[PDB]
Amino acid sequence: KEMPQPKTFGELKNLPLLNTDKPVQALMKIADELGEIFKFEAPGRVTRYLSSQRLIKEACDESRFDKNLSQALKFVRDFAGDGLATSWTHEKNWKKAHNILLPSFSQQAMKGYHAMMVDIAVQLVQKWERLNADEHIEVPEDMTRLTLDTIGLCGFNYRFNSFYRDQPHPFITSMVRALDERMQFQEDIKVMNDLVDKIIADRKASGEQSDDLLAHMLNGKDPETGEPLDDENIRYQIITFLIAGHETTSGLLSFALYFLVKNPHVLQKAAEEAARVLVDPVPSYKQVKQLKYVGMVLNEALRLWPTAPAFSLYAKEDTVLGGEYPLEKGDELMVLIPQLHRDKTIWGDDVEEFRPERFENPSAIPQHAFKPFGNGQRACIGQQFALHEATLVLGMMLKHFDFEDHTNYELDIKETLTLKPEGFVVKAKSKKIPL
Ligand code: HEM
Ligand SMILES: C=Cc1ccccc1
């Protein structure tokens, strides 16, 4: 079978279609028009965009397809090197760092992060308790303050102190300008390097037994090779986790809140759970695990707007995809996750409705139908960290405040490496429950 291809532009082929600030949303509309698979060509390259669970289930076969570095990740690799997200599976440092860092996301490790997640969650609740009458909240801005502080503190024992600031941290500013200006740069790379230096120097100076992610980066040994990470790769991993560890979680929290204010019955059901479960001034680990409906809200927000919306794969060998599309070794595929998550054959006709109850019986979901954390051994290592943080925080938000969509906010999805509802604002009226 011959694959459909969207409109072309002479020798530029399909390239000009990506000349937009919202390329994923542009590719979603192309998928709506052309279906489960289309060819996308640019001078010198081809990729195939997949949107159905029928095809993505095969693409996720690790015997046949491995993670490819997208154009975006190739650029990110200029700063994150062979850290986990930007390494090829076949690079020695991928498996080495994978093995060393996996224990930093075990159940025991998650329980270890809980108190420091609460520290930051409490700073967010106090900020909003302290606003004057009629003041509003800039949602993605505050969520980014919380998620950046949480990975800094939990992962590295470093305080970004984002809630003490009006404009984001110089690390964040430098990380954007500096990569930006790769597709002053001197002073920016210096901001990044200095911070990495400091995170390392301070742990080394401290007379501190710690079992955090940094501790594993610095001291853990890979059981396979028996080697620890070398200093160059540790730096890459710190950069990798400071970024990967916060931007997509902030997106998720922002979309979740957006969907709750747009669906007041769902908000009321989630708020009732928060009030029933979170019976103490501080949530416990056990109580966060009992926020089942809040977890479903989060999953349903990842269904509609997965905040890392695409991942790339290459064919390990010549193979046939879906009984119909022959591929050659090296051929690239792109999984368009928001489109996968709208596959009517899986989810029913109401795919654009926000209905967390879709996730009541998750064993009913077919293989590879829901992929917001990627696939296989190259799946998100931080999935449980993101979900624990976002469950804790959204549960606290719903326990402490009523929310108003006071502007009747029109969804505007800004695309970076991640997705966010740009300009999303709300008002939060305190329920006056002490911390
Ligand atoms: C809701 C929030 C998050 C989402 C949706 C998400 C999504 C993803 C996706 C789709 C991938 C696969 C990328 C690819 O195949 O190219 C990935 C990998 C990765 N993520 Fe996450 N992520 C989230 C949060 C986090 C957090 C909190 C951390 C760190 C604490 C993190 C660290 C990583 C790392 C290191 C990888 C690379 C793993 C490897 O290839 O070995 N992510 N993530
Ligand atoms: C936030 C985890 C992650 C990793 C790679 C790309 C986008 C997101």
Image (cartoon, rainbow, N blue to C red):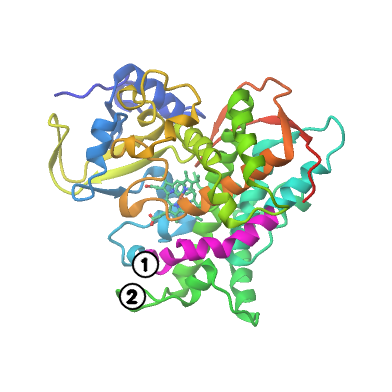
119 sits to left or right of 311? right
Q: Quadrant of the N terminus?
A: top left
In the rendered structure, which amino acid carries the disc numbered 1?
Answer: Asn
Give whichever of discs 2 and 1 has the lower sequence position.
1
Q: Which residue is at the far right?
A: 132
Tell me if residue 330 comes above or below residue 135 in the rendering. Answer: below
In the rendered structure, which amino acid carries the disc numbered 2?
Answer: Pro
Q: Residue at x 38, y 63 (%)?
A: 98
Which disc, if any, is residue 99?
1
Element on which disc 2 rests: loop
Q: Residue at x 38, y 38 (%)?
A: 362
Taking depth in this image into account, of 342 and 348 the one nearest to the observer is: 348
3 sits to left or right of 402? left
Residue 37: image x %, image y %? 26, 27
Dot 2 surroundings within 10 Å: few (below 14), some, or many (20 or more)? few
Element on which disc 1 rests: helix
130 sits to left or right of 187? right
Taking depth in this image into account, of 140 and 271 the one nearest to the observer is: 271
The answer to whether one can see residue 171 in this image is no
Q: Verify whether residue 337 appears in magenta.
A: no
Which residue position holds label 2? 223
Q: What is the span of residues highlighted in magenta in the rendered image? A: 97-120
Tell me if residue 432 comes above or below residue 96 in the rendering. Answer: above
The answer to whether one can see residue 288 in this image is yes
Residue 122: image x %, image y %? 72, 52
Q: Are marks 2 and 1 in contact (CB under 8 Å)?
A: yes
For the residues labelled 2 and 1, the Cα–Cα distance comes to 7 Å
Examine the image and state in which quarter residue 343 appears. Answer: top left
Tell me if residue 111 comes above or below residue 412 in the rendering. Answer: below
Residue 341: image x %, image y %? 39, 30
Magenta: predominant secondary structure element? Answer: helix
Taking depth in this image into account, of 319 and 362 the one nearest to the observer is: 362
